Image 1 (spheres, rainbow over the protein chains, first blue to last red):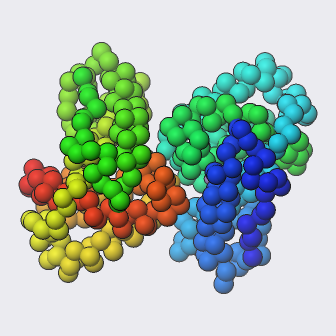
Image 2: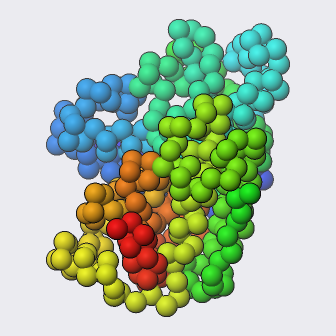
Image 3: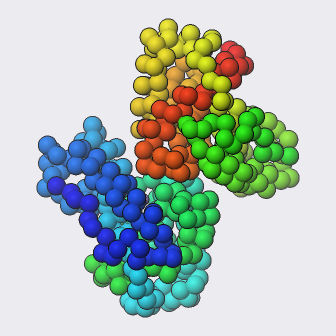
Length: 197
Length: 198
Ligand SMILES: [Mn+2]
Ligand SMILES: [Mn+2]
């Protein structure tokens, strides 16, 4: 059954951009809760055999009695699993995806600008994503723990913009959190998820 | 000319149920942002001077150039305006609505169990409500800053279950925040909202 994956770095590795208090509570309480509630919904069903990607890609096929719980807690597991890996203490703005971004948006900054506007515009709880749609790049956001895989789009970069992702250090200033984020993006992992799609 | 309302008590009045840090930033920054953005959104229109209740009950009528901004910021202004007046340091579990609740749910704490279960279950950002629906009591939750007035139900009690409302004191444990809330409910304001409804 699903386990809370360890972070690939220590709680403090992403300072000063993401504070150790938030990394610890966000990983060990919030993500752990999604794993517990996901397990309680799937265990004793034929969902036990499927990857989270498989489940989230096909939420409409899930039996209605557990669909909401699998949508919310399944989305939660997948989103944070992606997120912990898309962060690094050794961010470098180079690679296959950084190059695709400059051809399409005209520069990395212009892309960041549009990502930031959508990320900030996401009202309430949700995620800002870079996706592949029909082999093209697209900036989308989703509400709560919805994931663009449910709409057949492949996520290659994600930002958590639930208040719990930035309240400790940035309180009500989501745009400053979005700015700090660029400093910790694992562009190696963005390339790997793109090269998969 | 929409305005951030004053708190009718101090930032410490709701301790230890809601912390002074939260009361201060929730009102002074979060609510203030809704009021500022609402005033900006409605500039030049008949919305400038309408009651926020009328506006939110008639979101369908709002021109599409500003509908989302007024849904989000107008609802944030109404919701928080109601919320500050529905909290008090002198909560007493009595009156017209407590009596109707005991008739309908059997007791007040049985009602709290149902309210607490729906308020816990509202996934992501939102509100838990007690509403008047065609003269009857109903518990409902809404997403984000959506308000039951839009669906023709009058809110008489509300609880903010956005993470900002409880994160400083309770972190992930929204149920512990929901239990503390009962200690600071202004049942006199609930009765007044009920009577304005009926
Ligand atoms: Mn999160
Ligand atoms: Mn609030």
